[PDB]
Amino acid sequence: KDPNFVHSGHGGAVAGKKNRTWKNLKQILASERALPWQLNDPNYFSIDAPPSFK
DNA sequence: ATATCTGACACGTGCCTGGAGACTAGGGAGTAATCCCCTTGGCGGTTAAAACGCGGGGGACAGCGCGTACGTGCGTTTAAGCGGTGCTAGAGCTGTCTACGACCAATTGAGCG
Image 1 (cartoon, rainbow, N blue to C red):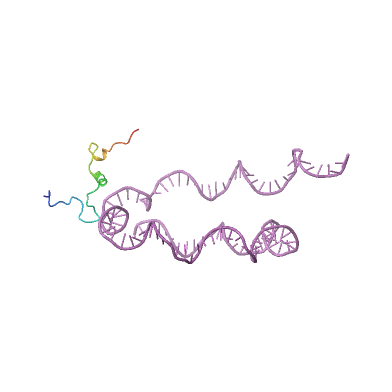
Image 2: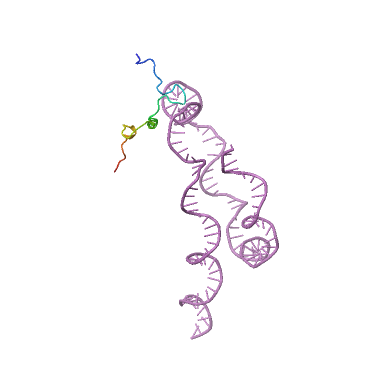
């Protein structure tokens, strides 16, 4: 039977003009910028490859 | 044969078009102050988006018949020149008044309380 019969409200709402989905990726890599990041970090903004040099 | 003609062939001055010089002074170009703008970007009441089951009617015939085409008849159409002669623009000139200049009032936008 069901792995659970009741479930949490993880961030999506029951009702409103608000989502049922959580924040999409474009809002995540925006809102994550407010944190105390440093020059040595595994920061997901920094991993996208550079432009082609030739 | 001859009179005298039609180029040869040029500088006369007219007209206006058209250029460059030296001036004022109108206005364009350089700039901050600063505001307020085009713009970036999350929010949820509202409609783009596509099935299923279905209503409105698109679709292809047969053939009736109120109009449509040809293209010649025949008498009515405009053409056509060139008479007179009033209109018509040129154009020469006012004789002002009318719209555009020079001096300064009612009404507005800006400042913030």
